[PDB]
Length: 119
Length: 119
Length: 119
Image (cartoon, rainbow over all chains, first blue to last red; front, side, top):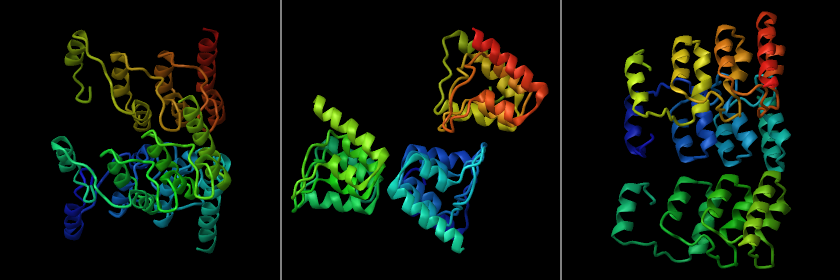
């Protein structure tokens, strides 16, 4: 995945494979902080849990919402990631995005909240 | 570049190579609308002009600002892209970003405008 | 250090060895989650700065106070790395320690914070 061998990774999952990551809660969050999109997208298709919680109970949705990243949150909401979660002190990912201030992200967060409400 | 073989892509640059495409301004903004970042990043590594204008006098800055790609905005301005340009009818990229409404992008646009003012 | 052999580490640092690691703030706060006191105790012997912060600008003091540790907090307090630093959530580590509880360790943390504030 890391070295751009997406073609090779197709055979491994076809024959049966799954990456195992220690500190997966913060490993996903660190990638979000980096800003790379292709690397994040490729690992998401491998079955990694988008709702992985770090040591401080922080889903990767918070990092994208806090940093204001828009495209990086499109894949996350496309993987049926939870949007009604809470932080260590208690903060919804939609509320965190609204707290920072982003009109474009507010509509996307509202649609995600509506989808979660509809279930 | 398209296949991601940056190992061979950098080899041709050292031996002497460049991107020879038609309608550079139109090609760049279409990639921005797609949202891919790694492919966009590798394009700028070859020295492509980030201020190439499309058929309607639209720099790639307008597309990123209008849509709201915050991560792509940093990459575009990292190549000394012009920020005081105008659209066909007349609209600065900072004004276009401000018109859509984005507090995070406004600060980034203001810093870009300050850098252009400082020159 | 990971292999528990400090004899080599003492010789290496004597020759002018510097402990530099990528995203040191993230690594310095995930260790306290596992409770590896022995690994952390020898970590401070190499002069690595314990004031580093993760992507959320949370020092290891913040997570240690949230985790509710007494022995681990004592060692980190002795390092004298800040007293009350604002995080992304805006909560001071002293407030987090008081909110968590542990009056046996809260008083020690408050006394350590008061000593650091006095200096």
